[PDB]
Image (tube, rainbow, N blue to C red; front, side):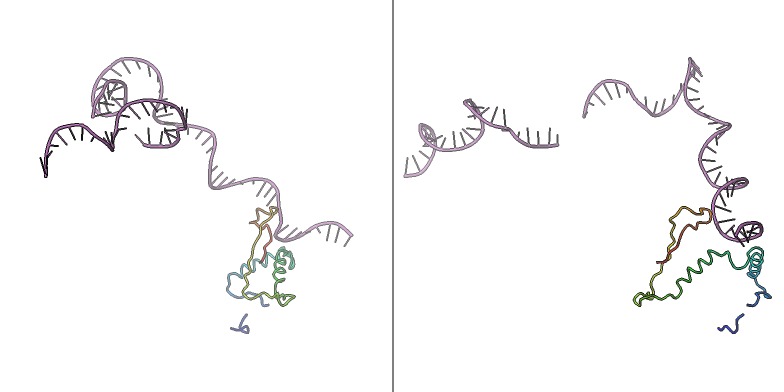
Length: 95
DNA sequence: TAACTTGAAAGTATTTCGATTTCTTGGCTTTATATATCTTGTGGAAAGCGTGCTAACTTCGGCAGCACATATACTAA
């Protein structure tokens, strides 16, 4: 179980299944998507997840003890949104 | 310092789909007339608990019972 014996290189020249979908997506990207952008919500999620990576408290007494319950709670307050798009109305919190 | 080609982002529109409505069927109701018959739909006349308070005076006012006393007939000496 090492990395020196593990496959950067173009993922091709092997009998695969998902690689066909991957190449189709690459072609669809080269068609209209330009460089690496238009991923607004994607970068939002990325940064909002990185904001909580390895941040230490200002005081030593504010260290979260091991095993503390973290609960994810979505909230739907507003009516002003897409009732059509599967429903994505409002923010989600952690407590 | 704009101009056009980008992207997922709305309404917005139309197309079909669940469902309830609307449209068809019978058939019974009712109108008279009389024709006729089974058991079972009746008409009608009998007859074999439970209390409370006194509303209070007056002056009965009788009898209930009771009941006390005793005069008398029976019995022991």
